[PDB]
Length: 49
Length: 42
Ligand SMILES: *[C@@H]1O[C@H](CO)[C@@H](O)[C@H](O)[C@H]1NC(C)=O
Image 1 (cartoon, rainbow over the protein chains, first blue to last red):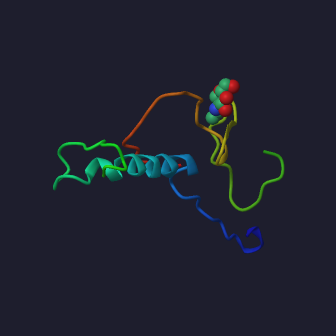
Image 2: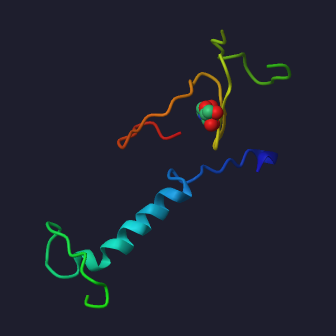
């Protein structure tokens, strides 16, 4: 990379940040899946979802 | 600061090179706060 200055910008979140993003969507897949819109939450037992 | 090249120094050195996961910064100062709306991505 340095041989002709091939600087790679790291993604502007550290790996843990989109890890927590994936965590949030993994917690909310059931949490959205009962009613249209993004108003309430639906943290139902996942098997019931 | 020893072995430089290109143009001159952009240095206002007076306090510690901060060690970061993105390397090390001259000019910043260590702190631990929280910002959810960052405008300068380092
Ligand atoms: C700030 O100080 C803490 C305490 O040792 C250290 O863990 C951290 O890496 C420091 N951060 C920077 C940017 O110097």
